[PDB]
Length: 306
Image (cartoon, rainbow, N blue to C red; front, side, top):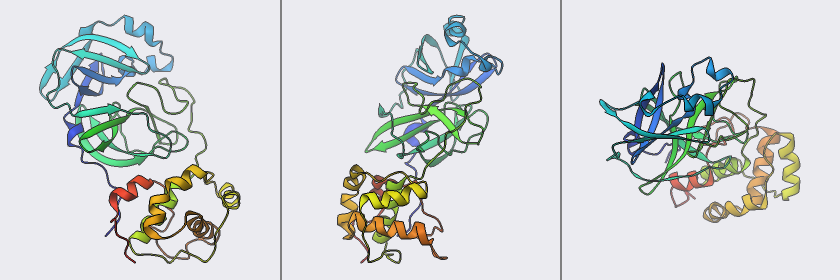
């Protein structure tokens, strides 16, 4: 029993974190095999960040312009190249702790674990959801750039996020491990701001299924709804439209609980229109949207508390 925002064990990632310094700028890097990946803005000073031309700034650097430190050991850079918004620093030693891994670009609404790091030293781990507006509500301080996001599938680490910037509202923006930003953001100091966000409908439904699996049905009702009628309510409450693909994804949870997807949608519609009347669901007083259908199946029992 219980239901918590649960991160994946971070050990496999901790062994890959290093520190990268260029000039007076230091941030984190990810060391896999003989390559260290880090934000390319490590080559920028606060002043360069106003209007950096990375091609021009990088051509002025040599391999020894970069200092890479793994724990107490200094790694020697023997090559460098830029890939989108990341730098790939080839070093003379292969990381003996490299786990089996993959680079994946996650989609909006999906979740991942973040290993917050400073000076190449892991400091904390927590779960984040990629918001529909392509930002994440992380917890980062100066020096956290290069910290990574990941999911673990068996013993394979699927890296999906590298941290690059904080936006005006305190939320965060970054790239996948190929250096492509999530969202319309860029790695330069501009007036860019997070666009309007929306609640992740599929995740809210998944979590309501989790509540039933864990033994709570107070919020269910005798009604059903069509996808279109549900979506009229979703637009009013700033929820993403429900799609048939979402309905299909919810099949396994619907099967485990015996509650048809559109019937759970009718329950959600009522919760949105009437509120929760002082009650809680899985300990929460609000509708949680940062657990995916996969997250629920991962954490909840496979047997419903009927």
